[PDB]
Image (cartoon, rainbow, N blue to C red):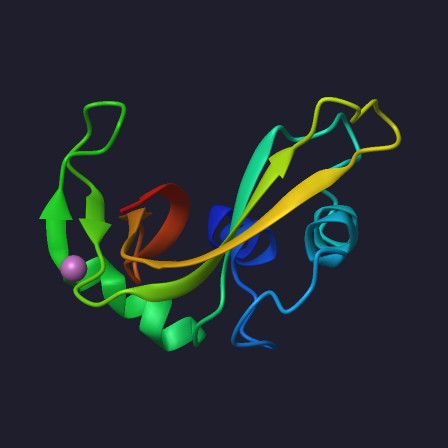
Length: 124
Ligand SMILES: [Pd+2]
């Protein structure tokens, strides 16, 4: 019983660095975070910000989730994220990732008490 909230931390938080300073980054990180145990996860996003900052988004701009739910919120300022996308030559269990860096607003879905993120919906 890993909590969705802990699951969110494992899958999307990386405060430890302020930017994906490497092209290794995704390869390492996707494997490190167990996003390659069942299969190659096609796409994952990592957020280079404090946990409190990312949790604070849960009381920022309420916006429609991609699945039609009302429990998504958009960051007021941009955040340092790193998109990991799976390449063509990625074959499980040799999962390989094109690292990509940007500053975009994030959008997350929150739920629970305390009200915290359990899902990364999009960057904008
Ligand atoms: Pd903006």
